[PDB]
Amino acid sequence: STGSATTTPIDSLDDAYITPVQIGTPAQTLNLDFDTGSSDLWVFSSETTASEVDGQTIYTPSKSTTAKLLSGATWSISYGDGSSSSGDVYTDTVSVGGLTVTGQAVESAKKVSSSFTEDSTIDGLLGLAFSTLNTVSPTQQKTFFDNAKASLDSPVFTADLGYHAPGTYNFGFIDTTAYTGSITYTAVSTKQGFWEWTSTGYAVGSGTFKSTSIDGIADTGTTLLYLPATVVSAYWAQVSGAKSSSSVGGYVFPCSATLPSFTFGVGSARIVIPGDYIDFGPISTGSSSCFGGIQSSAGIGINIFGDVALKAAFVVFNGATTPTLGFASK
Ligand SMILES: NCc1ccc(C(F)(F)F)cc1
Image (cartoon, rainbow, N blue to C red; front, side):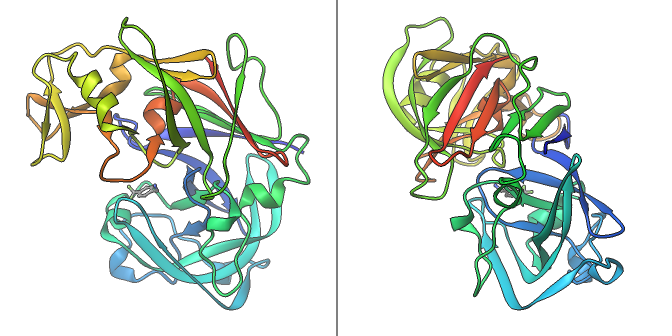
């Protein structure tokens, strides 16, 4: 079996992407943020604290004939940006673009942090990292991808994110019309539970390629590209007037500047991120200072290939016995 769903940016900056998901019987459609950096399927629900809901579509397990309360199970998650949520667990039927999984753990939020309340367009998250990161206690639960795996024609999912435009998440197959040239595959380490891989280097604009190992994670749930301080400094040194600002919390640049492109290596292949993708607009309404899409990972502890990098390529997440990541130009 296969699945295919359109993913759409939530705003004009591509801060996040939402994909419609059918949960329960009869179907209750919620717009979820597909996150390859986490492993919990959690949703806003009829149980969420009323004051912490501001425009989101909620899941109502009492209206679903296939919803079962997972007796005694709880969940609690803390994200890298300081956001969090927790609650109880149900099992229900979940479908993504025609691909159906019965008995999927649907984590019902009882409490959510302000950053989720403020994002009215995001009804929850669908975790696509390895199931070892799932927070359900006392019995850990599997991700949607892990449950669909045996039914899929091929144990893969692909991410084709659009730049200021809709894109696609495919499950079970590789659309050969979605990319140009060849797909280059690279090894994945599952030791930390992420789609962790090693980039072979970088180039800034039309500069010389610098061969250097950059260990990082392919994360659809993170907006920006977080790279080592040395790399980020070399990129922003090519933008006249750019500087790191402690009040803003990162590199800012004059909104009138032209940004050079950024190239990252995948084995012997190169993925070029156009400079326009690195512009995240004014730091505040009316400001002539713009926020950069390439920031330092020194305060995070891990390098993150977020939406800025992934949207410049067709990305294959191969969940075979030995996982690999494929990258192709598009
Ligand atoms: N990396 C997971 C993640 C995704 C979205 C959000 C936000 F912005 F919606 F709160 C926080 C954390």
